Image (cartoon, rainbow over all chains, first blue to last red):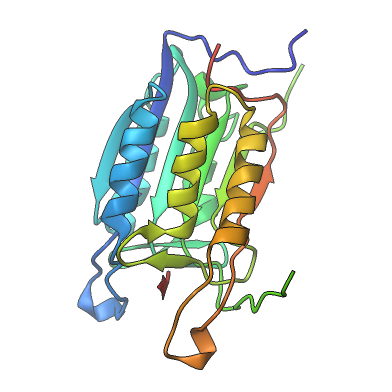
Length: 235
Length: 4
């Protein structure tokens, strides 16, 4: 059978990590304290999964687009997959460069099946730690293929909600993601790993704030899958 | 804790 992506190419693939911590004063966006902890954790976690990791810090929206364009124009024929990690401010459908916003659609389109042929039929993973709006979760006590196929978006939070980051320990989502990848990459299919990430973020984290509006809030991550096969990081 |  062929229910799983071929992951035994000579290379696992690129892991591009865009780490935006400091923003242009004119944007009025706050510094993302704790994001370096996230970036270092993802670097180490994906290095051990045998990805070629490229860390990028504090990119403008222009730099983000050009980087994605360039990476998409690379020959990935010897690569099993592609991973892109986005750490920034955001809103619905949007990620922030240091000087202003970027359509998530614009970035991901570069990797469409018809636009990056050396990635066609291969899993393209986008991992996004950024807000998707301003809602807060109060909680409750207990032969052609489509050009959009083979994408997976691991969002940190539900549609329309804030996403939480701790200035000391890093973002809830990324710390949980890394720990689950470390413990389970040699054992579970990726969807099942991300379900455990969901549970850990949902159960183990709750906000502490002096501001009643922001206190005692919860978060649930959002897996969006257009994959056509099971994904195992091992072979 | 802070929001993104």
